[PDB]
Amino acid sequence: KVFGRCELAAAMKRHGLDNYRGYSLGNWVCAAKFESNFNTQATNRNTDGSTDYGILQINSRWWCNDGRTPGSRNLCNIPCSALLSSDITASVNCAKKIVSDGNGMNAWVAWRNRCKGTDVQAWIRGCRL
Ligand SMILES: [Cl-]
Ligand code: NA
Image 1 (cartoon, rainbow, N blue to C red):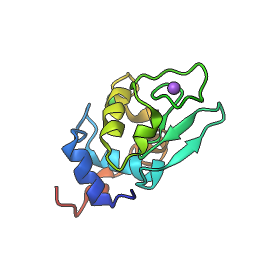
Image 2 (cartoon, protein in one colour):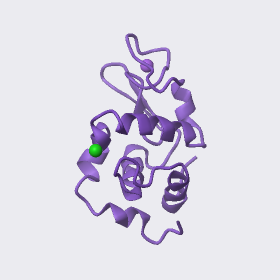
Image 3 (cartoon, rainbow, N blue to C red):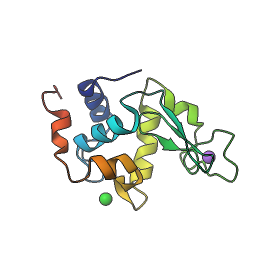
């Protein structure tokens, strides 16, 4: 599923991301935009052989199991494929664990490089929330 901006803002809000560990909703929408262009089915491979999955590009090296990342961890206890669902629940729940691990949203490179320090509220402007 390719989410619209406000559609996604509302789904994330419903799933408890607004102000989760101090990150306003705009932060999450912005990250999703630049990580996956709002596409739940996004996948990208990394040099180390790991793969990033879903709307928030969660990495198989530590968070999910894809059966092809030797030596990896599965800290969200889920198959990576679950992160590709049109239902963002698994992605959100795992993201909550990631953002809570000490490094905040810096775990998401696109967030750090394209959202951090910007006017992220612009991403939810005009949306009915
Ligand atoms: Cl933080
Ligand atoms: Na893994």
